Length: 470
Ligand SMILES: O=c1[nH]c(=O)c2[nH]c(=O)[nH]c2[nH]1
Image (cartoon, rainbow, N blue to C red; front, top):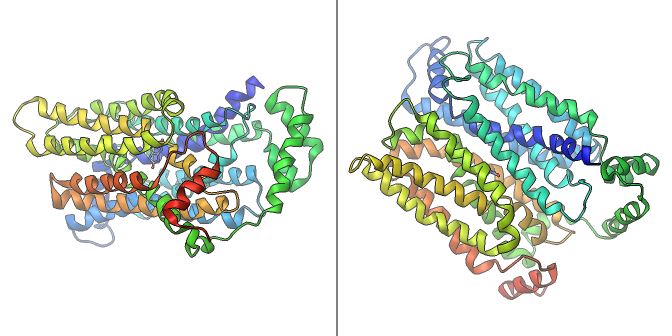
C-alpha cells in the first residue's frame, strides 16, 4: 500500500534516527559535561581532577558507545534463534527508554556512573537497531528497487546527526543548564518508533519460514503490496527457502582458517576499518573542540557547525544519481583518494591559521569537502559491497566478522582522538591521513569492478589474485 510506504519509512526512522543522534549529542555539551565532571570526583573522591585523566574520563565516556555496539553484534546470534524479528525490534524500544531515564537522572544524581553505564544502554541500541534493520527491513512493496533502501537507511543517519547540532544550539536547548533535556529529548523519537511498531503489521518472510502461518501472511502481503494478486509473490519466497535449507551454514572460525578467503577476510575488514578510521566519526564526535583550535572566532561555532551535517544530508540525496551511473569500484576507490589530498590541505590551514583572516574560513571549506567526499563516495557502499562479496553460505557469517571490527575500530578512533590532539597539536590529522591513503593503496590492487556482475567473475577475478583453487 502507498500509505504503508510512509509507515515503513517511519518504521525505519526511529532506529536509524537514534543511532545518528548519539554520534552528535556529544558535540554541544562537551565543555558543559566536563564542568559537571568537575563537580564530580570532588564530592566523593575529594581532590581536583588532573587534566590528563579528565580527558580520559570523557574519552571513555564517548568511546563506550562503540563497545555497546560490539556486544550488539554478538547478541544477535543468541537472541535471534528464539526471539522474533519484530520482537527483537520491540526490545530496543525498552533499552532506549531505560537508557534515556538514566540520562535524565544524570543531573538528578551527583555521580558520573549513570552517564557511562547509561550510554552502554544507548550503545546496545546502536547494535540490534543497526543489525536487525539494514538487511531485515527489506520488505518494501517493489522487490526490484531494494537498492534504494540501502541509501534510505543511510539518509536518516544524516538527519540523526543533523538534529544533534540543531538541538544543541545556544538558543534552542543547549545552555549552561537544561543539558539533561538535551539527552532527555531522545524519549520522543523512541516512543514514536514504539507507537509505529504495532502500526507496522509484521515481517512477511519471517512468519512463513518460522511460524508456518501462511493464512495470516497472505493478508500481510496485501497490507505491504496493496494488490490483490498475491500467489506469485508467496511462491517465490519459498523458492529461495529450499535453497537455504539445502546449503550448509558455515561457522565463523572456518573463514579465518580457510585458504580460499586468505585475502578476503582481511580485505572486507579493511574496507570498513577505513569506515571508522576514515575520521568522519571523529569529526561528528568532537566537532566543537576541533573547530575551536582552527582560528575560528568564538561564539559562532554552533552557528557554522550545521554545515558539517547539512551537506551530509544534501550529499546523501545526491548520492542516488552517482551509484548507478558510476558503479561501486571507481567512487569507492576514488572517494578515499579525493579526500586524502584534502586532509593535507586541511593540515595546511590548521598549521598557518594567521596569514590571512580567510584562512580559518579556508579551514572550514576543507572540512566540508571531506563530508561531501564521504557520503557521495564511501557511504552505504561497504554495507552492500560485502553482501555480494561472499556467497550465501558465509554471508550470515560475513557480518559476524564485519560487525566486530566495525565497533572495535569505532572504539579505537573515539578513544585515541583526544590524546592525539593534546600531543600532535596541529599535525593531528597526519595520522588520519596515513590510514586513509593506506586504504586507497590496499583496495586499489585487490578490489576489481563489482557493479552489475554476478558472483562468478567476482570469484574468478579474486581467484587469480588468491591462487585459491582449493
Ligand atoms: O551514512 C552514514 N553517515 C555517517 O556519517 C556515518 N558514520 C558511521 O560510522 N556510519 C555512517 N553512515
